[PDB]
Image (cartoon, rainbow, N blue to C red):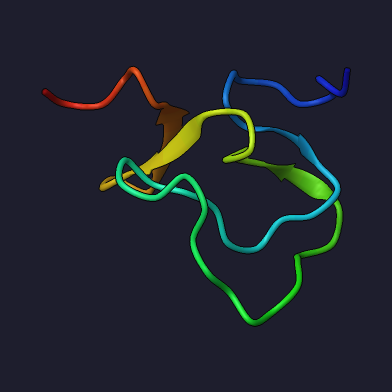
Length: 62
């Protein structure tokens, strides 16, 4: 209910900062969040690729 971005994955988020990976949907972070802006969404199922590219989880290697 907040697709105000362009390319897939990168979607609007009210709290940026840290995210998830192909091994940790949620990464610990004493900080809080980055200002509202287009970015990845771990709470949805998106992870960060070694190429620093946010991609769905099913888009991971074997």
